Amino acid sequence: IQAEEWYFGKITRRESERLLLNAENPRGTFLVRESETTKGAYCLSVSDFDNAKGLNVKHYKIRKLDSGGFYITSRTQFNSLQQLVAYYSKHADGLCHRLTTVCP
Amino acid sequence: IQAEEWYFGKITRRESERLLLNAENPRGTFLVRESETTKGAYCLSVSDFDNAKGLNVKHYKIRKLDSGGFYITSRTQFNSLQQLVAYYSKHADGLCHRLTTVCP
Image (cartoon, rainbow over all chains, first blue to last red; front, side):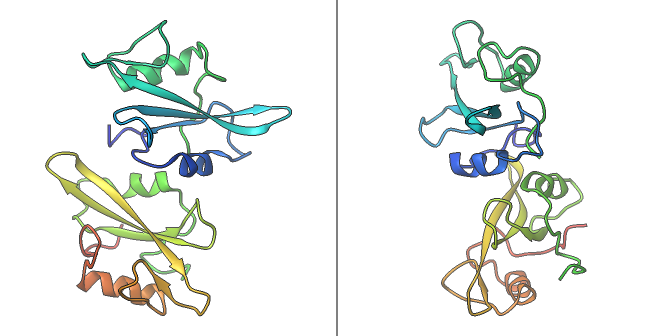
């Protein structure tokens, strides 16, 4: 995964909000990074646009089940991080937008 | 500096890693670019690898002093990015590896 286009490793929440808040990018642009906060968790930061809030980034924690799996909600779990990005690129299922472009 | 072989301008953090993470590059291949995230600072991106994570890129911010100079640590300051690049080619001096190859 150090070699996945969307995996930005251990960047901070500020760094990802800086990399993502760009009005030239389409909503649903995203990156997967490590959670600063929960040791062993990942985060899926996605930009969105709300008429009022304008451009905003949302952060979804991704927890690794003890067996190995990954989940954002109870509806679905993925056996890998790439299956999770793949699924949410086709179905938002709760996220603000389905994932479109990987962060530039 | 726009024509320096090692200077890669405004490329993104993500594009720098795409350039550096490649089998043809020695540990210590590098480039200098603008920091996307901190206007007015630069960034020295260096390829490295370990037998655990494989090839990975380390990013070191380069701050510009108001008096002209540049630094990555309090140990030494440099009057130009040319000076900084030459110093870290002879000495890692904090960095994961001394600078060996200008990124192709």
